[PDB]
Amino acid sequence: MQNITQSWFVQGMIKATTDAWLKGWDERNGGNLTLRLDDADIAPYHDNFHQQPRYIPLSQPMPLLANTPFIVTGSGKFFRNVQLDPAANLGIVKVDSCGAGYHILWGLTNEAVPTSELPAHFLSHSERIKATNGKDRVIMHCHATNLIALTYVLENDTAVFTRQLWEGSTECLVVFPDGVGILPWMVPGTDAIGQATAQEMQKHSLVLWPFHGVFGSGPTLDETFGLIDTAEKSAQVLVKVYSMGGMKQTISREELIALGKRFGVTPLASALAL
Amino acid sequence: MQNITQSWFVQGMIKATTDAWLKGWDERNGGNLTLRLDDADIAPYHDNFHQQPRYIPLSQPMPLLANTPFIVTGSGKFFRNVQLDPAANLGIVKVDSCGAGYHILWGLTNEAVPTSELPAHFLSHSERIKATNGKDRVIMHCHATNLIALTYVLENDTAVFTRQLWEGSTECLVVFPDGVGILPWMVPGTDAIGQATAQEMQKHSLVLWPFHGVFGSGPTLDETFGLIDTAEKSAQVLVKVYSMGGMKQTISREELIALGKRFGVTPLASALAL
Amino acid sequence: MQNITQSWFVQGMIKATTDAWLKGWDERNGGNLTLRLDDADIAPYHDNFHQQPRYIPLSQPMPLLANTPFIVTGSGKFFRNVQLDPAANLGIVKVDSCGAGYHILWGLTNEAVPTSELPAHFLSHSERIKATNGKDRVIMHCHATNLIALTYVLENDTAVFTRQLWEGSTECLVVFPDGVGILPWMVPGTDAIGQATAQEMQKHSLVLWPFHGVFGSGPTLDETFGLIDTAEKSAQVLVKVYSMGGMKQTISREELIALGKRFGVTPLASALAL
Amino acid sequence: MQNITQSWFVQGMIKATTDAWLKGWDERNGGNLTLRLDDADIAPYHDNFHQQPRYIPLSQPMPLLANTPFIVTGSGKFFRNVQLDPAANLGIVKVDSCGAGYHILWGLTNEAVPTSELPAHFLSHSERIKATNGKDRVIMHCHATNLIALTYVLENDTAVFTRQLWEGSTECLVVFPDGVGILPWMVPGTDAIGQATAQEMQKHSLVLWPFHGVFGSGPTLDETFGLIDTAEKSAQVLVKVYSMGGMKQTISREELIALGKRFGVTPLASALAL
Ligand SMILES: O=C(O)[C@H]1O[C@@H]2O[C@H]3[C@H](O)[C@@H](O)[C@@H](O[C@H]4[C@H](O)[C@@H](O)[C@@H](O[C@H]5[C@H](O)[C@@H](O)[C@@H](O[C@H]6[C@H](O)[C@@H](O)[C@@H](O[C@H]7[C@H](O)[C@@H](O)[C@@H](O[C@H]8[C@H](O)[C@@H](O)[C@@H](O[C@H]1[C@H](O)[C@H]2O)O[C@@H]8CO)O[C@@H]7CO)O[C@@H]6C(=O)O)O[C@@H]5CO)O[C@@H]4CO)O[C@@H]3CO
Ligand SMILES: *[C@H]1CC(=O)N(c2ccc(NNc3ccccc3)cc2)C1=O
Ligand SMILES: [Zn+2]
Ligand SMILES: [Zn+2]
Ligand SMILES: [Zn+2]
């Protein structure tokens, strides 16, 4: 029998980390990746399961994610090294039936632990199932080069930042009609910043952090990568245009209304009012 | 018998799309490619043709493309994965006797359909055949990065933009003396955008969609790729000098007038006036 | 038996050169890279050892490096060509028990000689041992594109340069809390530059050569790569922000101390108080 | 301000129970009804809300239904009396932010509590959101007079039972292509019967309990009533024909394929096999 590394999800995880390394958003060990699975998916690969599932408690209870398996990226690992050693960089966990801990059933070899952003990754998983009726399954974080440079010149508010991104290209409005949410500056790695991010996940599928990076979610990896990929391309044009002397002509407010009606999308009221 | 995946026109598609994802042009699902073929080309590959060709009516009758087969890229597909699975992403179609629709013969599995810009393809394919006596065989669309940012700062004029594009490099004038078409901003995926795009093809081989991208048309795949990339290089040259404070010396009109007649080429008279 | 070229350190250094090759940092033959080894790491591979080891005396005595084996690159050797020929581009040397000479054991064939900057690498190799108690093992030098351009604009003072890099990315204060030291411009390849470069290595892990390149040290082959990669990305963001027109809001001094307080890193007082 | 008793959802809950009383399926206090609302629906009626919302703990957590309001019928109430005193027979509940209980805001005066079959209603509400993508909102239970008679004489199996009601009338195929579910006889009002009912709701929108009654689901009250109404009328002609001696000519298996293909409806596999 083929080992678990030949499964459909493991091969998918290599594709995401390999291509992000060529894009240039994951210098050193920046970025994380988590995926949601089903109990039927991992059924044939019971042989690979470790004989000692390590148990790690949860920071706070998550009743909604009871008996839910995930495949995550280990902490302190290089995204470029994932394609070379899947066993030592990845792993699978399963949330207990109570919602206060998980068991490491494979991977994370040599006392490796999941990403330190797990409280942010798990809290946003819960708030997106409710807002999508169990469709979104993937959470991704990356330090988009063109998005970080924007937070130093643009006002740090939800309205104007979302409006600016809509004018970067035509397809931007269609992909994320709900806009993006930007927080004030906060120290990473704390639960106080995970709650704020999870609060903004209730209304948007794209989250911005000033001077740090970006957050996104989607149904599958291909659709999740496309959401971030489209967002960064719009930022690339703006930085190039802004250094030329600033914007001169752009899409009018009424023009975006006509675009929204054709594709059956509802633009954000706050942003369109600008 | 050699598989259809190894044919010359299939190997042409895998080369052209992969060379566009590596240039940062086709984020998400942006981009499509239709190439005209002959009945002799598809004759040896009758074994792999589908036994139940689904019939899909065309929006408008196209008598000039009757009995003319085409190869198309699927709608909503990702240019990164075309090399990974050409059959699920590429397809072949054939126009019926009366020019009212088309049949699916191979590819486009799992209820896949040709690209949503198909009406914009056939309206321009028919016109380009008339202008160049059937030499044209490729239609290319992609989201070049530096090209789009030019529309945000320069006047959206056919003559003005072509004039600037000629001064960016010495080879640009010879490659496209006919100039590049420009259109107002409009909603994609409609037959109205198909008419306007095909209408301007009577006098230009390239059309620029503001804030969206570019439209290509040429005799073969190799020249079509280099037809737009020549304008992309002039844009990258233009972008760098613009941020420097402006352009101070360039090719003068008196230098340009003698250049074309060295090669015996007829320049665009409208741009020569400026 | 297995060739020494199939060991861990030979394959490991092949990665480091090729990765930096595509970044655009090491055109022609610029840049250097050495790694410290152990006697046990090379014990079983005496088969590839040269029968007669050539002897070269050191310019100045180095007592701390006595009887220690190293692996280095060759002078006048491009970083691209290494993967095509491991033997003709690398070499392993072992300093004598006195600290005055070394013998070439394997590699460096065809009268190959180590890099001309060997005094600068050996001087910094010894002095980093005192500071890190033998943890650091790699010294790297390469022409980082965006760090070179910064010295033309920013003043060459430790307090100003360190603060700007800390503000271009959140993680910078955690990666190099000691700051970056700046030297005056000197003629390369001499011994005067080697003594000043080592002088700054007592209080910095990143030393900048104006208009020439950067120096950095790391515990392993990958940590030293990320250290330069993290610092390069920070300078890349600062280049666009400064070129876009200016910098308007920033991370305040109160936030900077709070960020370093959480991760247990002491910022440089002189630059922090700015 | 218009009274809450004249709202669009209270006047719609009277109609559903009054109409079933004239059918005869709700003798004494048999049957109950629940409806899902939105927070905007009950916002204007804040004035009439009780100042001391009673808190009732739930048997088991229901995290998916957090912060969701409903309207239900009381326990031990007569369907005939709802039109006489709406405030004593109906009530408004709201699940808390965690999912372990609910409050009572209006109605159910003189210490009245919701129906004893709420866990069955709540568990089916949660499940049908996943299998339908948030469209089904209503759950109804009633004792069909004839459908009980069919159980005493027909084999208690899912396959033949589904196919027989499919032969009653032509519209039966279109309305419920997924058939009906039949459970082994268990004592009503238990948590075991609630879990078993929810499992069958993952496939079909009609559930049969032997000798007791029926369950239904739909987007609105009118659409939910017509599902059971169509099922009952189809079962009416069955016993009428059956009591005359049995069937003599019925619908062939072939005609079920032709009718389903006409309206783009995929029938059940096992039922169509018979
Ligand atoms: O109404 C309910 O929400 C509840 O409200 C009141 O409770 C408040 C507490 O009095 C108050 O101190 C505070 O609680 C904090 C607590 O002090 C902290 O220590 C921490 O709690 C963590 C806990 O220490 C940790 O062990 C774990 O808890 C799990 C628990 O061990 C495990 O057994 C299970 O709990 C189940 C419980 O055993 C069941 O009986 C039942 O619980 C009922 C309970 O019996 C009812 O009385 C009622 O609780 C009231 C409570 O009485 C009020 O005082 O309702 C409960 C739900 O039906 O079900 C439980 C779930 O299965 O799981 C526990 C967990 O879910 O994993 O984790 C704890 C969280 O990290 O934090 C709490 C919260 O800050 O605040 C309470 C809310 O106001
Ligand atoms: C949300 C859902 C839920 O049930 N929660 C919760 C709160 C408190 C709690 N306390 N448990 C406890 C307290 C003291 C001693 C033993 C157990 C358990 C669960 C939420 O927060
Ligand atoms: Zn980050
Ligand atoms: Zn496009
Ligand atoms: Zn140098």
Image: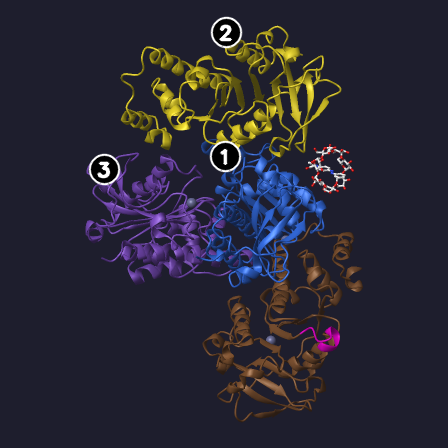
Chain colours: A blue, B purple, C brown, D yellow
Q: Residues within 10 Å of mark 1 (few under 14, many from 20)?
A: few
Residue D232 x/y as whole percent: 43, 15
User: Which element type, helix, strand or loop, lies under badge 3?
Assistant: loop
> In the image, is residue C132 part of the stretch drawn in magenta?
yes
Confirm whether circles 3 and 2 share one chain: no
Q: Is residue A196 left or right of residue B237?
A: right
Q: Is residue C154 left or right of residue D173?
A: right
User: Residue sitting at 51 percent across and 61 percent down?
Assistant: A83
| Residue D41 visible to an observer of this rendering | no
Label 3 resides on the chain identified as: B
Q: Which part of the image, by quadrant, shows the C terminus of chain C? A: bottom right
Residue A162 x/y as whole percent: 59, 41
Q: Is residue A174 left or right of residue B42?
A: right
Confirm whether circles 3 and 1 share one chain: no
Give the labeled residue for mark 2. D22
Distance of label 1 from label 2 (alpha carbons): 55 Å
> Type of residue at label 2?
Leu
> Type of residue at label 1?
Glu
What stretch of residues is rendered in magenta? Answer: C129-136
Label 2 resides on the chain identified as: D
User: Which element type, helix, strand or loop, lies under badge 2?
Assistant: helix
User: Which element type, helix, strand or loop, lies under badge 1?
Assistant: helix
> Type of residue at label 3?
Gly
C147 to D236, vertically: above or below: below
3 vs 2, front mark: 2
Q: Ligand 4 sits in which quadrant? A: top left
1 vs 2, front mark: 2
Give the labeled residue for mark 3. B99
Distance of label 3 from label 2 (alpha carbons): 61 Å
